[PDB]
Image: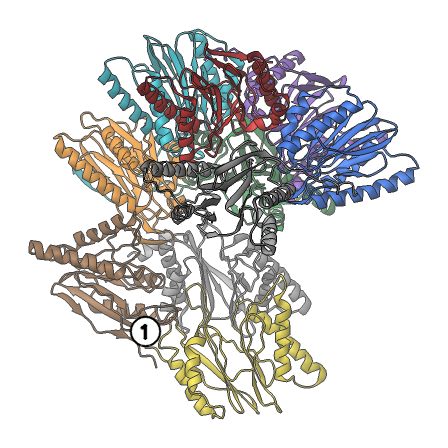
Chain colours: A purple, C cyan, D yellow, E brown, G orange, H green, I blue, J red
Amino acid sequence: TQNPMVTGTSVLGVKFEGGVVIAADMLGSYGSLARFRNISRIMRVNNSTMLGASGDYADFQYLKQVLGQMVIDEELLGDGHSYSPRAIHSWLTRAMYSRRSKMNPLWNTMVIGGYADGESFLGYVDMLGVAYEAPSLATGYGAYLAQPLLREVLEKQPVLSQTEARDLVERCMRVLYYRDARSYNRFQIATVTEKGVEIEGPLSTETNWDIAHMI
Amino acid sequence: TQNPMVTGTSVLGVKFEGGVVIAADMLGSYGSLARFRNISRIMRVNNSTMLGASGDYADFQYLKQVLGQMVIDEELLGDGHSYSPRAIHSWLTRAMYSRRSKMNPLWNTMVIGGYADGESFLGYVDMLGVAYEAPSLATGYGAYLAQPLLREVLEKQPVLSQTEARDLVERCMRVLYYRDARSYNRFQIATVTEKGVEIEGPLSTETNWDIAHMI
Amino acid sequence: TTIAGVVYKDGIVLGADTRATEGMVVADKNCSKIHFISPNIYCCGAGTAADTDMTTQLISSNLELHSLSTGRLPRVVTANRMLKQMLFRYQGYIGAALVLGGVDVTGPHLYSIYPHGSTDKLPYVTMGSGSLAAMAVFEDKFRPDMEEEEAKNLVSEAIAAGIFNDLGSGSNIDLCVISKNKLDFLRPYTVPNKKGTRLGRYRCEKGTTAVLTEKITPLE
Amino acid sequence: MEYLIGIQGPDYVLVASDRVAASNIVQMKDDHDKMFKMSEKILLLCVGEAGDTVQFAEYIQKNVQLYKMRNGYELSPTAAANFTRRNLADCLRSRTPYHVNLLLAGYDEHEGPALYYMDYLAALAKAPFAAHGYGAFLTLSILDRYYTPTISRERAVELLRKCLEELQKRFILNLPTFSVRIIDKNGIHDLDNISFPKQ
Amino acid sequence: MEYLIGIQGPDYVLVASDRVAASNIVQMKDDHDKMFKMSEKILLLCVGEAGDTVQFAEYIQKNVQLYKMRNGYELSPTAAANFTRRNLADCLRSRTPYHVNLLLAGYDEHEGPALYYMDYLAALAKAPFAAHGYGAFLTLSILDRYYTPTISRERAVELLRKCLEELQKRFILNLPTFSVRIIDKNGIHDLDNISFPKQ
Amino acid sequence: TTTLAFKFRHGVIVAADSRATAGAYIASQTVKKVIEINPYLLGTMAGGAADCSFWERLLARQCRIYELRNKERISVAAASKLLANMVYQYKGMGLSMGTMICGWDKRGPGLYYVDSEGNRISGATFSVGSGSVYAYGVMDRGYSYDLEVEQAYDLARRAIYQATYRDAYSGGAVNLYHVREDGWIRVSSDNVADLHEKYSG
Amino acid sequence: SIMSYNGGAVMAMKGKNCVAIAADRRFGIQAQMVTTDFQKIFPMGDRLYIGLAGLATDVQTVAQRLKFRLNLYELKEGRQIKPYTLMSMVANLLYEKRFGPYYTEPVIAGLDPKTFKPFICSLDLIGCPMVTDDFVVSGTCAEQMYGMCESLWEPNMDPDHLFETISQAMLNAVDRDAVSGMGVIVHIIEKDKITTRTLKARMD
Amino acid sequence: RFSPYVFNGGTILAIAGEDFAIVASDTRLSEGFSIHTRDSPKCYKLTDKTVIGCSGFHGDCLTLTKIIEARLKMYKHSNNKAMTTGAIAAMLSTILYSRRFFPYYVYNIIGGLDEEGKGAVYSFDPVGSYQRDSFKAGGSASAMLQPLLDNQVGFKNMQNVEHVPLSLDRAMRLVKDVFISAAERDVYTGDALRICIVTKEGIREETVSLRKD
Amino acid sequence: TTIMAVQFDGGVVLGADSRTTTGSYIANRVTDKLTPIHDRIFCCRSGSAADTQAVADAVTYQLGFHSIELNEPPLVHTAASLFKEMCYRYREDLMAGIIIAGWDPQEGGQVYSVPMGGMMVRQSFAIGGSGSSYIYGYVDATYREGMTKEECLQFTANALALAMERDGSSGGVIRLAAIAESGVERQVLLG
Amino acid sequence: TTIMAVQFDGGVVLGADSRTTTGSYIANRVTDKLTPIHDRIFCCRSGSAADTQAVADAVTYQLGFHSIELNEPPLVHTAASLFKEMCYRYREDLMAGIIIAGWDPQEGGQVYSVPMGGMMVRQSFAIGGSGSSYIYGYVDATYREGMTKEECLQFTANALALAMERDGSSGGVIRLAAIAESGVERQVLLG
């Protein structure tokens, strides 16, 4: 994609004790116009991993299709073997690299969160193929805004609980509603544990405006 | 003006027996957006002449101001001498040429109509200073659309009556409402005679949509 | 470069970080972006350094002139008006990202100036390259009418988070506190970084370099 | 850059060239040879984009040798010239064009002598005296001043001497040595190398 | 385009130039003179944008004549060179820049000989032998090969002979005739015109 | 980067510097520029490093195949022709390559000059590189055909010294190879500063 | 780059009680050298020098312009000039050409006229001063000299180790550089006297 | 428009000893004026005697690492033995030239032991040249590090300084000092320093932190 | 230009203007902007004209062949998937503002939207065309969940009325379509 | 961004958001977008910020000096003429969407609009700003001639509400201004 038509916005993800929580909002913006106020920007991959993305939404629909077909094929092998989340991360990295080598990039910025075999996983995939692992990921303007909150709390204490992680995500999404022009007060939280993959509903934020009474 | 912001559209004017009728519509389109649906695009100059214009509306306000001041000055001379319409036409032509020689053009397309001393007058002034007299003028897309109707009826009969002229103007404004994309179904007719200068009200058109029933 | 400003219950706390990058290479490890304006008004700069320097020295000279001509304490709105009129008169060519703060008769007043001439009165501002991280920390942990040590800890925390994030940020952290009576100005507020002692003494010897031509010129 | 001249006679062709090989600003080679013997009575010279010259010699030279070895006999100069023009005209409208500008010199037993004239746009010409380059300009007036269609060969050598004396007189280039051929009913005869001593 | 060389000695300065006046492709004038006698022991040569040369000669020449006629005596070579540099440096940052590139050659009674070196960006230099242009490249190796600070003048003439023999050997240009000056305690002396016989 | 080569009565001399910069920044000081193709061929490095190394290595491949097919070592002109033919098929795509080919022949000495622009000429003296004109000057001073051995050594070594003294991109170490009738032989590897000590006095 | 037209490198280093400034000698047009005796370190009064790097036009122009204003100042006031004053003067002179900028990076190194206190600073092409305690550099080969001085500097240095440190730094940072070389001049000054040494650098 | 490349930066060092090859690299992976992570080691263990480092554009580094590992496995499954160091160098040069006309934006440094048991560092360029040198510093802090290794390892530009062979722990304090000194002025030098040592007995690794700026 | 699709309980309701423009000249005053693909599924188009015409014809081809091969009435999501594939595969040359709507026996009335990017989403109402921007206020203020058919017709009438009144490119005449199980009811209104 | 001015019988009513944006980052959540000039005349701005601030200050200067020299309360058309002259004279450097409103003793409540060109027109209601395009449907639907004050406040509240809801750049908080003979009544609402 040379010119991204309908973009999403920032995606947040952070590990915790025996799970990874990822939350992104539900807005599809064209230019400055918040054209699509009810869309899903998180795919719940089979049972151990989970995907969230930014950039062009159509390319995300495409990768949703392709990954769904690949997961269906391995589940129909019937061998008892699944994809590890790191294997999905590797495959997606190779996909983006083969896109950008032919000068036809998939305009995305993807975050892969997974929990398999005791170990949590949180991977990053860029459009250019830049890919790494991290204890907390943040895309778009989230890397400018909600990244220092993640790295602030994670430096003072490297592990977390699920409640603390969810509360921190709520605060970061509140901040992104505060200072992203392309943002919206409706987001969904998606969570992986050993119990499976769970998508919570379209939650909202509680804002403060007591600075407006200051002239 | 390098870039015209708020443009008008086509202006129609035609002589008749002892008078000149001019009609233009009342729309203030910005780009494609019809932003200002009640504006006046004809100035009724003192008693003998009358001005209508196209292009950038702000420059028309400017020339409205300057011409009003010049007319006020001669009326305050108290000599019993007025401006002939051709003198105003000459002055306005010199103004446009001195604008464009300094590479700062006034983005307009102006029509001057006047009746003084038995003879009608209908003058044209371009942005580039191209200026002439004509028995029927048409600006913008009017020179493409309502010009052949004027030159059609005027070749079969060189003079006209006031009723025939007004009816022909009505038909031409109907056609311009049919096939100008920047057009609007509300126009005002302005008329000079020996009785003075008269501005008629915001008339409309009667349309035919019987081609839509053909599939 | 990550500067910040805030208004607590009485006055103003300003901050800075003193890494003067030139392109991609650290050109300085100790600089000073908190500039003098008046005995009550200070200013911070960002972006092009020499533009901010010359502009703030001109306005500080003019306001010292005005205050000595009048015979009383300067006003912050006057500094704001001079700055916005000058920066608009230069059509946005001069890049000077300014934070303006002082205490007048009316009280504390904080202004941020964007280099075209657009100004805002705010209780707290951040400017610079890493301003986004400090604005995140502010929107997380701000409450109206804070006390002194709360505000100092907050601004230190914000610029510290900007230094642990941003790449053009990172040095020792400057602060400044303005009240109706007490002005403070400190060189190192909190020094987050240390440096490892050298592991090899790579000291040269007295004569290890060939010399071609000497000269001696005595003095008094 | 330079020019190699090709004066045609009644029953001989007087072709010549330089020994100059250009660079950035330096004269890398002062004994260069632009002469590509197609057959026993057909010569070829080449000036243009200097990577294409040798490969043109390869293509044309070797395909003419193929015709001669196959059918038993030599081409006419005219058909060979037209064959060169055809390969230029085919090579023009592609992704890989060739940029050369040289005239062709042959001799038939029946048609006698013949001079042709190319361009970087594949145009045939049948000329009494032709040119290319920048020496073209300063030399065709002198040549068109002193031309007779029935001119003898030593007069042509003297005329070429004169033409060179106007090449070394108002030119911004060096051009120290010129090699000179002649073609007759006997074949290819090499004349002496035409230089000037400098110091 | 060309270059005029300027070899400095122990008690003389050996400057040389061409007699070449370039065009589109033709050599319009083959006896051109670049020599602008500033004073009795200070010469000036000029190569650059060819509309600026005469006006530089006007400005510098006439202002030096103004100083000499006013105060009663001749400038030093150093102050004159610096004055040229100042007028370049003032004329650079304007709407009307000058684009010339030459070296200046003088002789003091006390400082002895002196050689300076400009550029189109108004840089002073105090050089033992300098260069500009394209002859700069092919000639500074030969000159820096055979240099002695205590070299006699006939050796310098032989060195210049050799330098010219490498100018006419691998250059894409003509350069047929060179004029040569010398400066001593007696003033401005002219040596013989240095050409090489063409035919 | 400045290389030269010249043939005379007793074979061919090849010398080069060893500095290979990157813009204004010097990468290394010991880049062996004279690429050893065979026990009878010597190729150079002229501008592009990767391109010269790769294409001359491919030429060495073709020559070894040629020898194993004909039981006779290839000539110099044939090798230069194969190199020019392989280089021409990428004209305009941005190859910078100005190498030289040296070796001994049935005819004797052989010295050719192959460009990325596809120029292929014989000759007696050559010099390639940014400061090649400097080498041209002092070499075309001291050149003859009837020369000795140590005379040619001093000529080539002094030539590269003058070139690196004037040019800014040239420098490092002066390599020196000598092509004979039987095979090529490395002469010496002399540093610049040692030559500065030798020729300053 | 216009800054990479003639090369150039100026290093200044603060010692214990003394300060050392050094620069290269090479002058030429971009790949062609011309001379080995181009002056880039100028005397501005006693025990106070300035170094200039970049385009040579602005080097000589700013040096003469500064000498003009400097002598006017030292004649209007009988005292000699303090180094902060010189720094502000160079900043004002460069900032007068805010939009007509000179292409130079001045480096000032001098002692205190009252005490023996050293002083170093450097400026940018628009007039941004920067006072430090260890070293300032200017020119094309910046990163080399940064690596050298952050590798070799000690706080309290006798003039011998100061001289050898700045010598080794300049030699190694210049030898990695291409367009700047051809000799080193070193000025090592102190309260009592002024020493100028030239090093045996690679002439390649 | 779409730009196909981006500069991730990084700094890789190599020192060839008498019987050891030390390769070290920072672990910051950044972009512009941000930090993506503070743990991403540039070193990669190819064989029991070969370690490669790759800086520059990160995706090409990952791709190149995986292709080199694949061809190593191909050589093993064809010829019953691991590659040498120079064989890997020749193969990598062929690969880096095999995408000439859409280049890798990758600096490459291979350290390791030769078959005689000596140190050998093969440097590279993005287009495919190589050379056997004793020490190289690749990446953003190249110019901050090459002259100091010329001063200490190469013994250049000094007088009456004898040539001592470079020992091991002396090389270690060298590597630590040059990364501290380069991290003072660089913006791309990481925190974690990952030092890989190749001996005749295996591969050792060592993690030394830095200032967290 | 300005196209609109609103579903209700029984079925869906479409609508468009006909002012197809080229530059500043009106080439055609009246246009069939909505197209019957199948007898129960419509699409209304925007953007370039030739692109959308060729796409609608090819979709008609594939969908007709498939629905005959099924020997069952087609789904709406199937046609939405076909437009999605053809839009997404050639995003580089097409400019399609295709909005799919239609009643279905299995799923009732549905409305899908495909903008220029080739993404596909289900909505309860849709806004398409360059002149729909001027009534995103009115379609967010006036819409209420659970209208009738006549209320949807009046709704889209007021919508396209204000859009034709304000935008210069929009205008012409109003075409409507009401789709339910009982049939397709097209009419041409003005007001 | 999104600014609004509605007159009624007694006086006028203004309104704006405060979401001043720069690029994609929100610089300020709350801004006095409407500016007092005289005690009875306001202006609300859009486009670039520094341009409108300097223009509003100079107009405040000239209008204050003139109204003191008149020793009479100023006209609204006078201030509109001042903005017209300063906008039109430098249409090469300014981007002003200035909308003037205010009650007058001689002429009652008036609303003038000055867009980016430099023209001046009198309107009964006005739409200014980049995100007003979306509620031209709502303001040409809901407006009725001869409202009360509370109806105008509710009207502009719903207007700026829908504009803030749809456009990304608009948002923040709602500021209102009510001008009559009795005074200026400002309040900050949300809903």
Residue matched to label 1: E176
Q: Residue at x 29, y 40 (%)?
A: G52
Quick one: which residue is furthest to the left in this view?
A: E72
Q: Nearer the viewer, residue E151 or I168?
A: I168
> What is the total number of numbered labels drawn onto the structure image?
1
Residue F15 percent coordinates (x, y):
45, 60
Left or right, C109 with reference to J167: left
Q: Tell me the SS state at disc 1.
A: loop
Left or right, C72 with reference to A95: left
Q: Quadrant of the N terminus of chain C?
A: top left
Q: Nearer the viewer, residue G12 or J67?
A: J67
Question: Dividing the picture into quarters, in which one does residue I4 lie?
Answer: top right
Amino acid on which the number 1 mark rests in the picture: Pro
Q: Chain of mark 1?
A: E
Q: Quadrant of the C terminus of chain C?
A: top left
Q: Is residue A102 above or below residue H188?
A: below
Q: Nearer the viewer, residue H164 or G26?
A: G26
Q: Residue at x 47, y 73 (%)?
A: D133
Q: Nearer the viewer, residue E126 or I152?
A: I152
Residue J72 percent coordinates (x, y):
35, 17
Question: Dividing the picture into quarters, in which one does residue I64 lie?
Answer: top right
